[PDB]
Length: 283
Length: 282
Image (tube, rainbow over all chains, first blue to last red; front, side, top):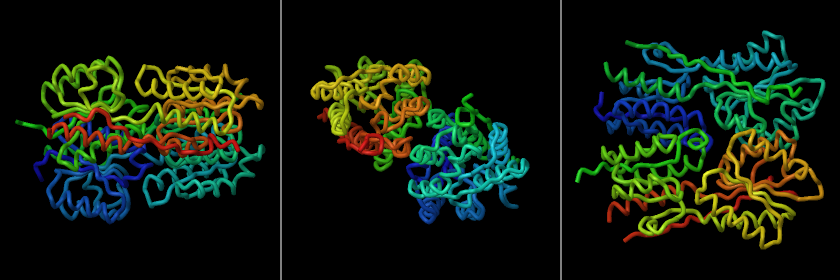
């Protein structure tokens, strides 16, 4: 191992809704403060696409710039996870183990099936007929896990449901909600919309405002990752708190412990449902 | 001799209303980018209150962990600004020069009197009869500048207006907006609400959603500090783009120039009006 006392933190992208995403802000704060309490510095990747991220992480390996890495995402056949495996770099992954070799490498995750099941159950407890899950593109394991938990509680209570995969584009979201507008306005059908993540959810609420689809009256809404932004959304949003500052602190501790020396295969951080106005009946 | 090649980045707090604000996120990216260009690293303060902040800036000085500081705010009688003048630390301020001694130090700021005037003018072009400016507590220089701009244009155009000071606390905001509820619902009186900053603005919109006061039908709304939070607000908001990344880069450049060397007193970064649905009542 190197002797830089620095940890490289690999991000998914540099995009405006990613570097402003309260998930990454809190995860990186969690990592950095822990690292900084033990004499370790941090270096966040700034790359915005896969070929460039393969380039800039390889630079960090070859120029011996850091001692270790923390991958801030999990994906099946991740070539940059393969890079760190090929070039013998110690690392942590924030996300779900997906393979045989993943037994060797410490992962830090939430239980994303349970989190979604908890959220999906709660909306059913308020009384719904039909459910909608809205997700983002990419073969991300967090997406797969949260979809799976949603589909399981929905099937368990024999409810009708649909999955919508969308980009964050206003026009694109608008078209999807235009299609549902008439059913979303039907007073005989009780509906709930669940989004993958709060940043995507905020775009949804904006389109729902534009179409005068009122919450909770026409539809109930909920999402993942509680922060100040879901708290002061229009209306305040029911959400699963996934403790991103805790996730970061735990990843920071794990990588430090690896550099001291044993494998802890998977560390699970408990989540918490926060009930707000968007799933609460006004009477 | 024995320079650290690090810059202390001093914020007022680190809680999530602050640290999730794309203004601070973008100014901090802007500073670091310019610093990491020229070999310098950065060290961002983590304290939430004034007591912990003073203690940690003092410790940064005493244990010499940074060469210089950037203050990411401007307020009169600032105790950490006084601490840096006491300890002769090289520093710059992001915000308005206030005091007699503030002549000595570079400030990087927006044209906040003018940008609020620009915003008030745009709202008035759409046709209004009354105007409300909502500000946050704590007499910062950015508040006074934005209220002054507002007041000058609103009085010039012979318009009725009020100034509301509030905390970001939900039930305080709710109480304020419930008093205006009947007036805001009136189809004969045209009104506009302007908030000090996008993050406070969002708490306002959420209370407006609660009270069934639709935008821009019942009231037009607008604020300062353009980001994704105003672009995808409910509804998208008209706002002043105050250029936080560029502001950060000019701060990064100003401090590196102070350490190399005779002091540029004020840098102004221009702002841009961004018109969206919330003021588009046509």
